[PDB]
Image: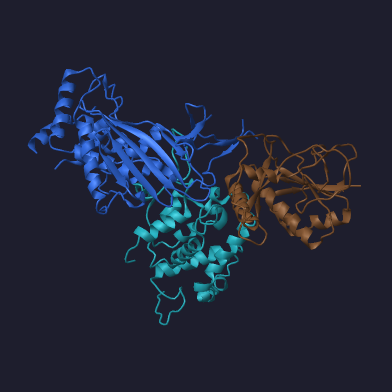
Chain colours: A brown, B blue, C cyan
Amino acid sequence: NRYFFAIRYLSDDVDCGLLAGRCISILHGFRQAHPGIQIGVAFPEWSDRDLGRSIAFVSTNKSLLERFRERSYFQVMQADNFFALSLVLEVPDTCQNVRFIRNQNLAKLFVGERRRRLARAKRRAKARGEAFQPHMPDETKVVGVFHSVFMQSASSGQSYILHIQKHRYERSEDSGYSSYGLASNDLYTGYVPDLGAIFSTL
Amino acid sequence: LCTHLSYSRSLSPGKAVFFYKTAESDFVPLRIEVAKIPQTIEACYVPPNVDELYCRFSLRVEANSMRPYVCSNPDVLRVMIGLAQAYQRLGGYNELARRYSANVLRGIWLWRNQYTQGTKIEIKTSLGSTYHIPDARRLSWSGDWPELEQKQLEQLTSEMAKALSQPDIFWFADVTASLKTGFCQEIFPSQKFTESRQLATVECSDGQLAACINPQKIGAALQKIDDWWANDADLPLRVHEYGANHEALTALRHPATGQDFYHLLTKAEQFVTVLESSELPGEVHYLMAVLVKGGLFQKG
Amino acid sequence: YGCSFESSNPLLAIGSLSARFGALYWYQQRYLSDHEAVRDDRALTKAIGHFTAWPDAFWRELQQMVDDALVRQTKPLNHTDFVDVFGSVVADCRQIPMRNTGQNFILKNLIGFLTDLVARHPQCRVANVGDLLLSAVDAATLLSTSVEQVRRLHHEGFLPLSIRPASRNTVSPHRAVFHLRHVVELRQARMQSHH
């Protein structure tokens, strides 16, 4: 009921965080052309120390996934021997699922985010008419492990980082993927198979 | 030369601490927040509703370059003593004092935190003087300082010229600066050296932590007054026996040129002779500056 | 056999014979890559027309490969070698035997271009074109001087070194180490002459 294909990086000096960002950007552009589609992003070479030198895409519609594979960027990168591409094939029925949820809460670890939050809070108080009296939290927080992907803004002058965590799957409800094929903590449920198996194919 | 020769340091700060005032208490520390995520992330910025940040440190100056801490050779000792005095009586300590004094009043010891809406520097000393620079953002290495400010540079130069040259004067300075700041401006304290990064703090007597700048980091800024090479003043280097330049990854007084400390150390007999005929040249200014930042000069 | 020209609008229509010879040699390796077929007349006959719009075509040839290179990027640009984008077009400037800019017109146009390229791309938080690394032999060519002079210029501190080498080693002439924007600015600032 599921199809996938994978891409591996051939060069030993490849920067995974820079390069991975381009594949996501393409997925986004495709999503804009055909709004009613669902394609998920998986990292079959995910590790606790690094992101890994490979990426894979998973979906349910074979004919649509083929169209994605035909996108010119991928074809060029293969021709110049930067990428190794697989063919589209069926997902094995003997595996387990993971989420790949992204966490925007981690933004609050950096000064720039706190500044913006407070500036808005001050201005917001004028409607209430009360004096601006902010109240700060304590000194210690605990967070999980995450990796970064470098991203360019869409039709603007900015760039920023995506922060990716890996959660184990638990089954409930119905699904949907975000514009980046990523999962959200709430109200964006989906999953991908953790295809670290049969990777000897590339 | 000889086997044993040492000088100790003649000029030194303690460390700098950041804090702010409230209506309830005069000393509230600026603190740092840490998230364990070990491998952590952390941040520090002035909190909402504090209009200005204070930074303070103390400085002692001692006339301790007049005599070798240790010397194993009676002939080396006779010369080094004659030289320091031959220099002292022609002046020249004024020149060194002028250079050190200029750096304190300018404020470069604030390193990366100089970018304020207005910085005010106040100095007090153990002899009863007070100095006031209403705005430190406009004073260059090279140029004529505005009136009433040029004057305090002369007055401070005089007190320090004495502190450096006559013994049994116990001279202390207490330097406080005020930084008028932005809405939630980021602050840059000293970092920790490790085998992600961490920041340095100190403990208060009540158990609170505070942000700080290390002693030698304040010191490295004060002694940056070496511009006697290649007849091109540019900006000054931190005094170093080899003329090291970290930004360009090079060395200006490389031993290959004959312009380093060790070649010059061996000509002392000739310099004393000249001073007696005296004008002070760059070669003796360099040497005196190194003796002030004392260390080991051994295994000749 | 001689020059004898007037109303010499093309950049190939002026100068001493040695330069006129060098310009043709350069054109040939670069655009007549087809194996020799002893088309000794026809093969070279076309070079004159080619140069007639040079002041406005050479730049487009250079621009085209900035974009094609960019979309194939794999590392942040501030660790990328200058050569990976421009393909040694700089070394080819050495086939004309003269060193100064007023006579070696091929080099004169390449520098013109690079100066403009840097000018429209000022420094910011994310690295961009203009931060590419040059090797010692490349600065020597752009600065119209021999290599030993660059070493002397480094030693006096007129320009920074960006890559930290290991100890008990040396950086060879072929190693890529200065930023492009640093070389372009230094040249405008202190290398000009009446040539």
Whether residue B183 sits left or right of residue B54 in the image: it is right
B179 or B91, which lies in front?
A: B179
Quadrant in the picture for the C terminus of chain C: bottom left
Q: Is residue B246 above or below residue B78?
A: below
Q: Look at the picture and state if C13 lies above or below A162.
A: below
Return the residue nearer the eye: A85 or C17. Answer: A85
Name the residue located 39 percent from the left edge and 67 percent from the top edge.
Answer: C103
Which residue is more in the foreground, B118 or B3?
B118
Q: Residue B222 appears in which quarter of the rendering? A: top left
Considering every residue shown, the one lying at the far left of the view is B277
Residue B127 position within the rendered picture, expressed as x and y whole percent measured from the top left: 24, 34
Which quarter shows the N terminus of chain C? bottom left
Numbered marks: total = 0
Query: Residue B249 or C10: which is nearer the viewer?
Result: B249
Quarter holding residue A15: top right
Residue C75 visible in the snapshot: no
Q: Is residue B230 left or right of residue B247?
A: left
User: Residue farthest to the bottom?
Assistant: C7
Residue B149: percent from left, percent from top: 26, 50
In screen coordinates, is B243 left or right of A159? left
Q: Where on the picture, by quarter, is residue C129?
A: bottom right
Q: Position of residue B40 (x, y in %)?
A: 61, 35
The reply to whether residue A105 is visible in this rendering is yes
Q: Image point 75% across, 56% down: which residue?
A: A28
Horizontal relation, residue B173 to residue A198: left or right: left
Give the percent coordinates (x, y) of residue A29: 74, 59
